[PDB]
Length: 204
Length: 202
Image 1 (cartoon, rainbow over the protein chains, first blue to last red):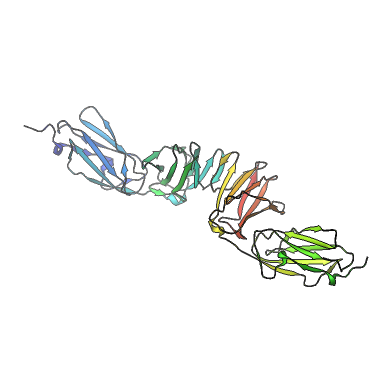
Image 2: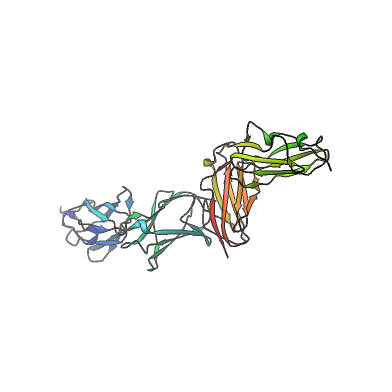
């Protein structure tokens, strides 16, 4: 009996698998071509440079190919394991280097709660359900984007939307929905900005 | 109106030659019963050389009770005169000693009903009350004191409420625009990040 799938026939390509490096802080995509590999489930696992799982968004293109996207928020080595029908595809695991860009040290951060400016200050205590607005001025930071990653008490890593105003500035809006310890990590071009990470405890 | 300052005697906890604990209000007694009739004056200079308020109670019996708050550690110089003449052993040089561990105090700021964590400034709004709660639960022996330096140069001793659970509340509203310096000490020493510099704006 011939197997229903053949992972050895899956082909991968695209910017997100460039072994010569990708720029940190920018979302990136790659393509998986399973048209010759029969019928199976495509799975993609990503381990970030700190050893934590990272979300891999898989889009079914309808024709036997798939587009996978992820956000290398931090610089360093990303390990991407790709399997089809439970079997690893050729060249997996991929080892992708996210390279730093710009100068995160030149970013300026100001925090506001309820319209009260706090400067580059947050916590240690925050209130559950109270929105925090964090503005990052990256006018002098050069090439790169601001990313915000929140480590939640339950252990998840949330990629928080960063509004790019194109002023060279960025706005971050976050509200802690549950009690416990959060780590609010703000990076530019893959590296911490001054005062990041912010460790906070949500209460009340 | 004859007086003799050389017959005035001064003693008490506030003049203890072995030292006093910083951050606690203290009192001393001036006995002028043998010194005739004259005006008593008490001038206190703190370790930074600033005048410190001296509350004088005339006891109506030839004696007076004087009280002051040594908010910071160091030498306090207390000059006492009767009828304009310095009394024996004046000026008194009293050492206020630190107590507890001010570095273990934790700050919580509240403005307009919002808890702002340990984040005071850089700006405050004129006429808007700020509540600064100092958690001294892990700081041991001592009290929280606070002095505010205003734009015009005045030095205001702000009354600090002791909640008797280890925490203290400071209430302050900036009435005028400009730069304020908020000094917060525990047991005579600056808590972390004190003094706090803030700018009052419209």
